[PDB]
Amino acid sequence: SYTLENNGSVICIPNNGQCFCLAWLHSRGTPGEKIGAQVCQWIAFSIAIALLTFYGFTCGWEEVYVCCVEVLFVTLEIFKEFSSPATVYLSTGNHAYCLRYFEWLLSCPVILIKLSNLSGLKNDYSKRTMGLIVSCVGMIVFGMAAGLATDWLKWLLYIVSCIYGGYMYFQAAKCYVEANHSVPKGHCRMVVKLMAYAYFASWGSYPILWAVGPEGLLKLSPYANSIGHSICDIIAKEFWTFLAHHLRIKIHEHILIHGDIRKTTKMEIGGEEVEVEEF
Amino acid sequence: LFQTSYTLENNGSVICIPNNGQCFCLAWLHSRGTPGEKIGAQVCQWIAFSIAIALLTFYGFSATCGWEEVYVCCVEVLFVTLEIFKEFSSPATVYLSTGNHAYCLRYFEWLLSCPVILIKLSNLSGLKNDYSKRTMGLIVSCVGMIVFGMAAGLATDWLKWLLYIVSCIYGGYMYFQAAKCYVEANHSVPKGHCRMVVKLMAYAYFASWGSYPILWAVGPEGLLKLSPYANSIGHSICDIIAKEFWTFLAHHLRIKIHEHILIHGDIRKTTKMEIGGEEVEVEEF
Ligand SMILES: CCCCCCCC/C=C\CCCCCCCC(=O)OC[C@H](O)CO
Ligand SMILES: CCCCCCCC/C=C\CCCCCCCC(=O)OC[C@H](O)CO
Ligand SMILES: CCCCCCCC/C=C\CCCCCCCC(=O)OC[C@H](O)CO
Ligand SMILES: CCCCCCCC/C=C\CCCCCCCC(=O)OC[C@H](O)CO
Ligand SMILES: CCCCCCCC/C=C\CCCCCCCC(=O)OC[C@H](O)CO
């Protein structure tokens, strides 16, 4: 595709108008790693289609939107993952997977909008809901910039992203505590706890996968990193929204057979005191 | 950085560069604008820089009442500073293997500021716990709008304009939701000075927000009429209106409503209104 010159110090290429960089030609992963990515992609696709069909087509727009985004994303990844602009190849020699950051920006705020109102629909939206959304957006923005950036700048932006993420994780964790005391005593408290465990395990893995992936320490290949992101998406997008959809109807069914008995009880969760709904 | 040194050798159809692991593309060496446009860009940058700092000093630093104005102007201070010193360095400006370039620093600016503006717009009146369901429709539609706009700038050829249209569909739903907020804000603030402020915020919002898709389609990520410097002039003027003039009025409005209630007392009446063909409950003074 090119030609050497001198003693390897000069390289010549055709003047055809196509950008050239040897650093863009690195391998994508091993044959076994590719097969695993294909397997997990089609599982994530097939589960989303099923969950879309289960949800239907309003109350419950969040789950639909998240799963619609998963279908679109996983479909574009199956067919045109390493094509620009799904994967961007920068003049600095590196590359970034912009298709994935776009996915996060569409779905992560919605998941958090669902989290701030897990229990019986309290239309009064708090200042906490805004704190989740704003911190999540800032987190992904500085994450995406760190993926495009290079050398020390990359890790400076990465750290800024972790600061945003911390506030988001903090606010998200306070939701799960308030959500627990706000749902019926039996089966509903377990689902909230299972949703919390699924949320932190999946959402906690992305920074780890980022730092060792092809946009960080270059340990994991793109194909390998794809397997890891597919599994997190299955838990964060599909398993979690199913539990959220399930939690709603179980709360509705409990109310029609028990009523709507609620007392305003005040307690402390984070560094403050909050009054929450109690059955 | 890319390669700026090369030699057009052979008949001109074969080019040679030093083999130093440095990416090379002639399409990246395009002009950034004229000396006049360069100056006009720098004038508008330092104006936005200075107004943002004055507003930040004016609002003062008190999850507080008025966090939106501070965050927006903080995003302004960070964006303009990075644009003044490192506008055309990567990743502020990204140069793709497809020959095109994109101003990612601007999309980052939008993603940080545009939702917060709409969060403020969702609650233009006083008090708290006023967001509800329109807010989410504003945020989700605004975010999707920027996301598909960013993808459009990264892409080339027909895909770019496909992504552009999808962004406009997102934007139209957002613009629609936004207009109903101003209609409801009019009927929920004191019938004197505050409604003139709300109407002025509405004009500034649409005139500034409506100009970004026009600048985009015509600038260096579109039909290539406006240079990067020229396109910077237009964006700075829109930012001064969208982020600085608009948040000052939002900050001013909140004072005027609080000063009104402090002397007039809190009196209200719930009115079942038709906003965009539906039953909306808007409380009036
Ligand atoms: C009810 C609505 C139904 C909607 C339709 C649902 C279709 C499910 C498709 C595949 C499932 C997984 C089967 C495994 C697919 C292997 C595909 C393959 O050959 O590999 C991918 C290829 O390499 C990439 O270009
Ligand atoms: C080369 C230089 C590149 C630029 C590098 C400098 C960037 C500094 C900006 C912000 C610091 C991080 C502040 C993170 C703000 C999070 C606070 C927040 O918004 O959350 C509020 C909370 O959730 C409700 O209480
Ligand atoms: C190798 C390990 C395989 C792990 C694969 C994890 C896939 C999770 C995907 C989506 C979540 C869907 C969860 C919903 C599953 C149905 C369970 C259910 O709720 O059924 C209720 C009914 O009462 C009982 O018959
Ligand atoms: C309570 C705290 C009160 C704080 C009070 C505010 C302090 C302002 C500080 C720094 C601004 C100085 C930077 C001013 C930038 C203007 C530069 C300019 O005018 O443009 C010329 C250009 O730099 C030619 O290269
Ligand atoms: C809070 C309100 C304060 C608002 C601010 C008050 C107005 C500042 C004056 C002029 C605008 C910018 C100054 C124009 C100078 C730009 C620098 C420049 O033009 O230098 C280019 C030169 O060609 C390099 O070689």
Image (cartoon, coloured by chain):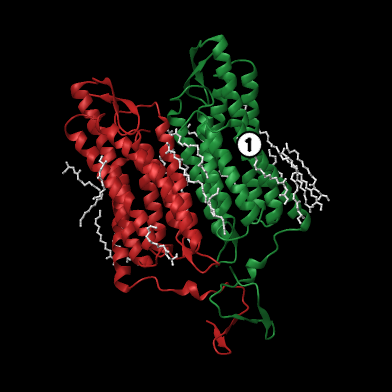
Chain colours: A red, B green
Give the residue type that dot 1 points to. Answer: Glu
x 40%, y 46%: residue: A165
Q: Quadrant of residue B14?
A: bottom right
Q: Which residue is mark 1?
A: B244
Residue A194 position in % (x across, y down): 23, 42
Whether residue B117 is visible, yes or no, is yes
Viewport quadrant of the C terminus of chain A: top left
Q: Residues within 10 Å of mark 1 (few under 14, many from 20)?
A: many
- Would residue B156 be found to the left or right of residue A185 on screen? right
Residue at the bottom extreme of this rendering: A7
Residue found at x 48% / y 59%: A154
Q: Position of residue A2 (x, y in %)?
A: 54, 83
State which image quarter holds ligand 4: top right
Q: How many marks?
A: 1
Helix, strand or loop at mark 1: helix
Instruction: Examine the rendered structure and indicate whether residue B203 appears above or below residue A8.
Output: above
The x, y position of residue A197, in whole percent, is 25, 45
